[PDB]
Image 1 (cartoon, chains in turn brown, yellow):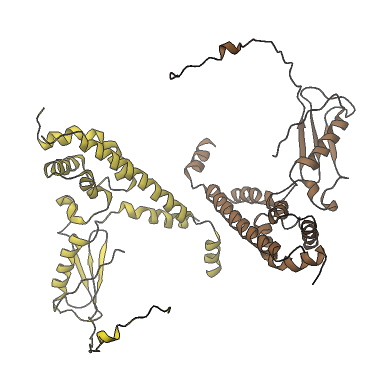
Image 2 (cartoon, each protein chain N blue to C red; image 1 turned 120 degrees about the vertical axis):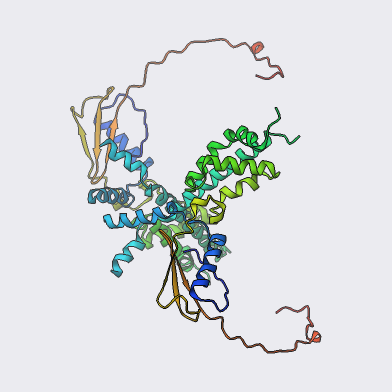
Length: 230
Length: 230
């Protein structure tokens, strides 16, 4: 349900959809199906077992609230472990055996590898960062003089689709679903859907409304103030 | 499962059981079956639905931990509400219309009645304090110059059986269950059970062990100390 708005001009549904995809790879966080599993299992669990029945759900124990709070606590714990690990690992090498940033990354990686693995498993990001990619970005951060937090912000948040590998984004399989012809221009109220392999960008188009402006003159003599209460 | 120990001399099981009952009405908190309902319902709920099956229970959500924490939070909230209510209600009357402590209790009770009712319902003590008894103890506290907390400590904790009304303790229906004759004296290892209408005092008797003492002489010359670390 990640939602973003975009102004466009007079474009066809095709061109508007392609601008939407450009902005999708730029702006939206990357599609992580692992982050979607819990809901599915919860739904399936309700499958394993109408107003009064919902009433009894409210009177029941909210497992989801406490599970989310505990998971948030665990994620913050793993995050602080990871920050300490990466700070110590960057402090293990001096700028000045002389070695290139690739060998420096390979030298300091085993002192951050377990904490990073645990954080990427607790945030379900382990399928998006291979060890080779982590070493590549690590030598990148060592080369460009970045801090542990600058290295680590790629791994803390989910991040958009273009942070990741080229086989990760399936630019080839996008499918434009429009009720009308896709060569028709945009108008108010049309809905087109850009379907990928497992998700879909439901895009509804609204007209930017007709706006009326009018001057009213506020005199700087009218900005008087008194010490009395209001 | 409230458990207390008592030393006794050479008594028969009858006399030891009666000392146990004297100390029961003195020392043990009063039998509250309402506080026992939750477990029963939980058991019945497990009835509504062997090592691996327990393993899966550990991997499940611990509803009881969070429910107990939330109930404790609610009890403390109601407790602070009750303390503020009773403090304001006692501050509404001066020692110095002139009225006896009964009418003073009836005058200040409606300013504490709702908070006290909510606290006795959240602690499941509403069947143990009638309004007449609360007014009686309230006029008692107003008479003897006690503070709001001194009035309120009867209602905060569960309290033993003799705080409450005379029909509350069923002194007449106690039943002594012993495997041997109850006129026999106590010895090591015997178990007798004092059954009331819904609970039972399981009492096991142990011998106070044979103790050997011996002098060792610690010289006050041997209490020397140095500033060095240990």
